[PDB]
Amino acid sequence: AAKLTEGFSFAQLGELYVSSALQWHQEGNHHIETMVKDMTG
Amino acid sequence: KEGLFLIGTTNYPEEIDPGLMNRAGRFDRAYEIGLPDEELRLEYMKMRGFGIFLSEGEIKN
Image (cartoon, rainbow over all chains, first blue to last red; front, side, top):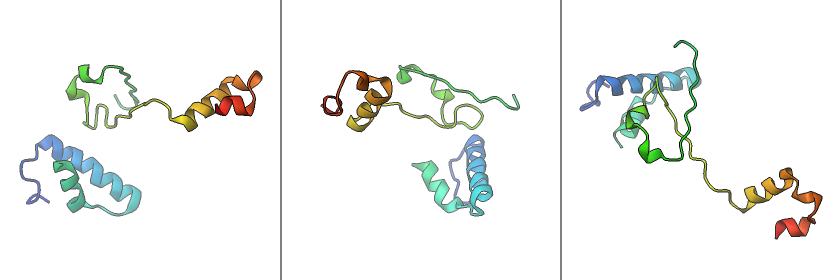
């Protein structure tokens, strides 16, 4: 995930944290791969 | 803060501070409240009381 997050600000890495955490808490799944792209575009 | 739910409201979203938006910790989601389609317009007229003086057909119309 460190590799795939080129051009991310720390803030955006934090906004990514809440999202993957919420899915992980809600669902038991983290789709890091899916969510970096959703954040790019 | 520890326990505040914020609800902001605007008719002029263009004039919102963009910094308000899409940060967790300050307005994580925005919702557009649009004009009603027919089904919603008809639902409104029913709960509002148009039925007091209009038939089911006059309300559909």
